[PDB]
Image (cartoon, rainbow, N blue to C red):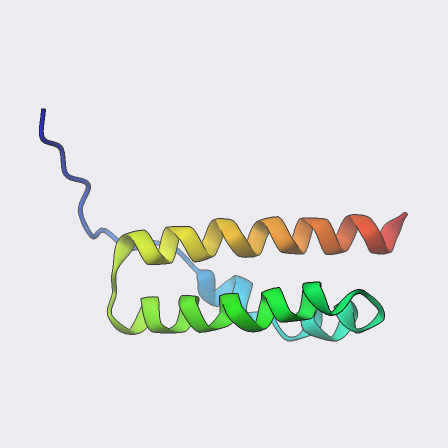
Amino acid sequence: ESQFHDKRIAEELRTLLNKSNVYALAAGSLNPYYKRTIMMNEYRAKAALKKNDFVSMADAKVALEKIYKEIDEIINR
């Protein structure tokens, strides 16, 4: 059974990558893992916006909400 989802794009990973730098700043009291993982998700997200690929955009989005949630948690205690 073949199936296709298509490119109707209504995601603001803009919104996420808008704070991608503030979150980078706040991981600077944490293991290098956290910053490094922002540095390497920013990349994916940007390329993905440029080629307008859906699946790369959805990935990166999930990735960023996850790491922001981790950071928040850690920081709030």
